[PDB]
Length: 50
Length: 50
Image 1 (cartoon, rainbow over the protein chains, first blue to last red):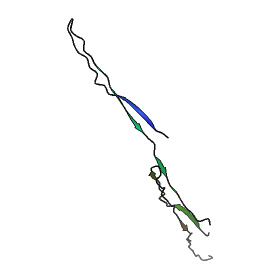
Image 2: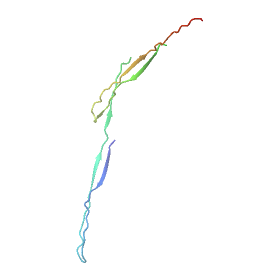
Image 3: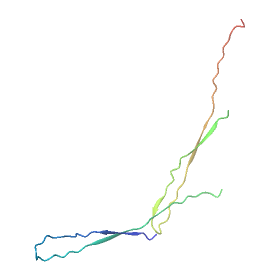
Image 4: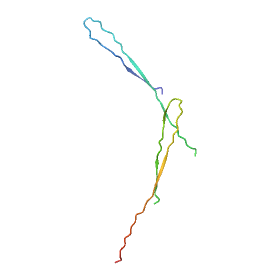
């Protein structure tokens, strides 16, 4: 009844070519999420008691 | 000899999507019938008693 949430990776992760004694560079990842909820379908029908 | 009656459903029943606290819709069915009776084929032929 409360619904669900879906995770998703989205990091533009990187790497670099370097020489001997060159400074090794720094990188960072990233993530997001999205949610989904149910919905109700319903109908009524009516008659005389006869 | 009296023939037959054939029933047939014809109703476009319906439902709808509703939010929390929306008030439900109302719907109705439908039906029909058809009757069928026989018919007679006949013929005569005639000859001399000779």
